[PDB]
Image (tube, rainbow, N blue to C red):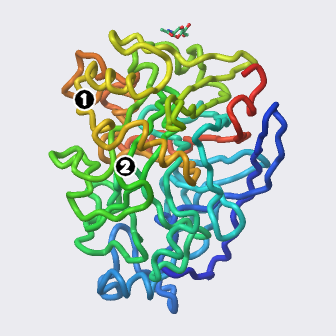
Amino acid sequence: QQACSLTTERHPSLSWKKCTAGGQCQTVQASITLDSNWRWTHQVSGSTNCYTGNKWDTSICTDAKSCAQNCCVDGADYTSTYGITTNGDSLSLKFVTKGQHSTNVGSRTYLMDGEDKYQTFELLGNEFTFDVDVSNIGCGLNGALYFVSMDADGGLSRYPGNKAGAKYGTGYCDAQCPRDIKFINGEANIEGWTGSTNDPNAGAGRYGTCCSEMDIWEANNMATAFTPHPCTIIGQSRCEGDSCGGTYSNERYAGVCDPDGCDFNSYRQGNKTFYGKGMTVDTTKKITVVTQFLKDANGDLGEIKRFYVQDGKIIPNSESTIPGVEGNSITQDWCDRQKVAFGDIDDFNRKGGMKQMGKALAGPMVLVMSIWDDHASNMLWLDSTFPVDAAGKPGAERGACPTTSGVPAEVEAEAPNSNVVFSNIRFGPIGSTVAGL
Ligand SMILES: *[C@@H]1O[C@H](CO)[C@@H](O)[C@H](O)[C@H]1NC(C)=O
């Protein structure tokens, strides 16, 4: 896609902390950008749209290549259109934002390093910490903070049809190989584009976009999970149709990425009252979330550890109480055993497991912060029983939300002003980001 400026693009400012041995930190003045899927997409000459509602203008976009060369994404009205606001070290994402002419649902944002590049993070051997307020996001919603192996320039140098780049939030990929992404590989994903059956603003195209994903935080006030997803191709790759994998079909595991990941959700792992509203990690108030990425003796990713801080108390991660699945952290052996115990296909191991994840963690990953609902599964995989059939067994119940929850139309009508606030990002070597740790 090209970039236009009918709307001046001003990345909202956000500071974060880069920490070093002993807990010294320096404040970095930075900013955020909106993902290209949410932007106004129109002809470079016109303001004639290339995409409206959930449909490409096929009288304008006649092929994937020319569509991206002749259409641009434009700047974003962060506050008024998207309900995206910052205040110092804090980023607030509102769920539904109604304007004069239209209503926006959800957002996905990236941390920037200057105007034209994403701030990359090399997680292996390091510790990523942030504060979060999930009190106002409930069943069926996800306020996510996570890492993906996107290109730092959003694909600008790899793909000549992409002139917008990281400045305009291009180049998204994740371990679900999503096919709803409008520009992939500098080409418009117009081929066989199918309007969503339930989302008036989304559709799905011929191609999907895959890459390694480390889900530090997929959460609402009822459930949270941290989940590495390895991919046999580390960085951003395009996949074709059903070979993509990542949906709930027979072809789920056919793509290069593990769409399930090896997940640690304390509720799912047998501690139903560790995390949630009124629980030990109490989602009705601000939480500090610490995630450490430990190397083994060979320098590979050996362990992923989680600690919380709330009201000054350091809370280690809940131990898993699932028989044969001992420990309060993610390791290869833990994952092997968890998959057996839950009866789940071990695609984590098949796609290279902890070691392959560590290959992505050793290199640059991009910080993603988003608020979204789930038109495919209603977020039941996060906070309810999933799949719905499987009710009475280890692994089935991931949170206390009823299986009625998460239908996008319902949550959008009943909780439009839902929001998540991410704040006080600190990143550095293990032991540098938080005192008493
Ligand atoms: C379950 O969480 C509680 C806090 O609610 C904690 O005291 C306990 O150690 C946890 N169980 C396990 C097995 O870690």
Q: Quadrant of residue 195?
A: bottom left
For residue 225, side relative to residue 100 (left or right): left
The residue sitting at the front extreme is 298
Q: Disc 1 marks which amino acid?
A: Asp
Query: Looking at the image, how many numbered discs can be counted on the residues?
Result: 2
Q: Which residue is mark 2?
A: 231
For marks 2 and 1 on the same chain, the one whose residue lies earlier in the sequence: 2
Closer to the eye: label 2 or 1: 2
Query: In this orientation, does residue 400 appear?
Result: no
Q: Residues within 10 Å of mark 2 (few under 14, many from 20)?
A: many
Secondary structure, mark 1, is loop
Pick the front one: 153 or 56:
153
Residue at image point 57% right, 68% down? 153
Direction from residue 137 to residue 239 in the image, left or right = left
Residue at 51% from the left image edge and 81% from the top image edge:
2
Residue drawn where x is 53% and y is 49% of the image: 370
Q: Determine which of the numbered discs, if any, sits on residue 344 in the image.
A: 1
